[PDB]
Structures are given as C-alpha cells and as structure tokens.
Image 1 (cartoon, rainbow, N blue to C red):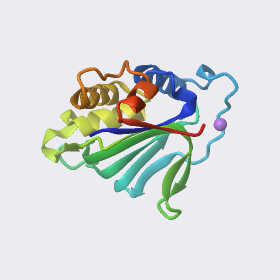
Image 2: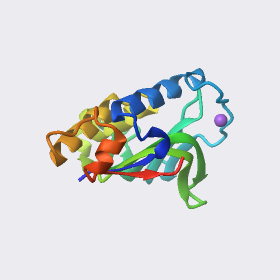
Image 3: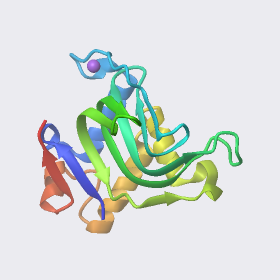
Length: 182
Ligand code: NA
C-alpha cells in the first residue's frame, strides 16, 4: 500500500492542496514569495542517458523539482516513440536537485512530500497511454493531475474514508503517512 512522507510544514494541508501549490510553484517562482531561481542541477536519468532507476527534473521557471524512482525507460524514436514507461515506485516532490548518477543518485535539497509504494507498472505496449507516462510526463511540465488521480485511488484502496482531500496528519493517523522535519 501507498506510503507517504511529508515535511511537518504541510501537516494540516490536504494532498490536493499540496500538489496544487507545488504545481503552481513549478510554473512560477512568484507563487512562493521569497524564493529565487538559482538551481544549476536540472536533472535527467540516473544512470541515463535514457533509462534509469531515477528520473529527476527541475522546473525552468523555479527550483521546484521532482524525482521519479523505479525502473524507468524513455523510447526516444523507437516505436512507440517519446514514451516514458516501466516501473514507477515513487515520486518525491520538493525544491532544488542535488547529486546525480556519479554522486549517489539524485536527491532534493528540500524534500517536501514523497509518495512511495505506488505499484505502477506500464508496459511499453501502452505507449503514451500508459499511466507511468501520464504521471511522469505530466510532472515534466509541472502538471500533477495524473499523479493526483493515482494517489487518490491508492488512498481509497487503504480505506474508503481516505482521499486526496485528507490532510497529511489524517493520513498519518490512518497509518499511511509519516512526518519529517521542515
Ligand atoms: Na532557489
């Protein structure tokens, strides 16, 4: 079942509220007053160049960033072309990337929220219709709608009462989520 780690900054926020804010910040640094854009590490595949156990990316408009973990692949020109597929175990969201393939993998300088044990596995046959593609390609432009829908489904699988409108603290009571320092 889904496991969620969250900075205590977000304890009283709902999952939907948090994803909306991260996505808005991905589109515009000004969404979070006080932040400046000064990240140099923009991510990529680890090990890469186009497959890895991680795919990390930083926004161009802000230092909002994410890291997808699992066993991931990008088809390039191979049919079905421009497809991101494979096993997606985790999505971590936050601000600024550090590391890389030769430095212990990618990490977030400030990890805000992580969603793990996602259990997503999209075969190459589905192409750009696969859920892994929709989730990770969406996040590449800061769009968290596909991710959100998968989190909602996974929460409802734990208990009918849980959803993306639950707070992180409510999800912690349910046994799904765990707080981290800010
Ligand atoms: Na910054």
